[PDB]
Image 1 (tube, helix red, strand yellow):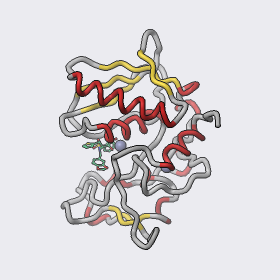
Image 2: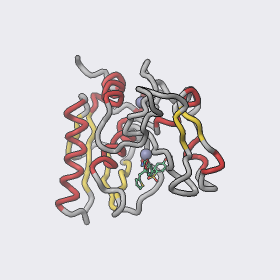
Image 3: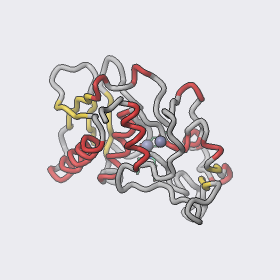
Length: 201
Ligand SMILES: COc1ccc(S(=O)(=O)N(Cc2ccc3c(c2)OCO3)[C@H](Cc2cccs2)C(=O)NO)cc1
Ligand SMILES: [Zn+2]
Ligand SMILES: [Zn+2]
């Protein structure tokens, strides 16, 4: 679900950042690990902010919606970390939003790939599952990525742990593909990010 908006691509892949106070050294290490992970697989770079108008601010706040997707023009944007959403994989995901990705399951073509089980969604949270409008996403010729760091789990925003809100429609290597990994950038995330930022081969 890569943004179609050219203004939302960070020029030259350069993303200035500020780490807010109140973070422990341990937490700051995770932020650096997450940023270096992006840097090591793509041409995106993170720079300590000096006088740039647009930059990201690691902010210590309760977990939940919402992040700005891509570069916000004319002011900073928060990347929010809380007690229960501070691990490497979650920060990598949030940096996915920063660079310009919406949630994978909201791709305009997602109905070919997953079913949404509406009756299992937490009332009021259905907006989490609405497709991006077709003009808001340019997938850059890349197929739907079940392994994406940006993909929800099977039971995200569900009425219960054992009730699925998202069910892949078909088998890959004999089984329905697992979704919602928060280990690392997928092969798909990297290929697509490289296209989005026009990274040198
Ligand atoms: C429409 O935009 C948003 C943006 C952010 C959020 S969120 O609540 O902050 N959250 C949803 C989430 C929780 C658990 C998950 C999941 C997605 O996938 C695997 O398991 C995550 C961050 C969090 C992790 C744990 C608690 S909150 C997210 O998508 N951030 O971008 C919700 C909606
Ligand atoms: Zn997210
Ligand atoms: Zn993708």
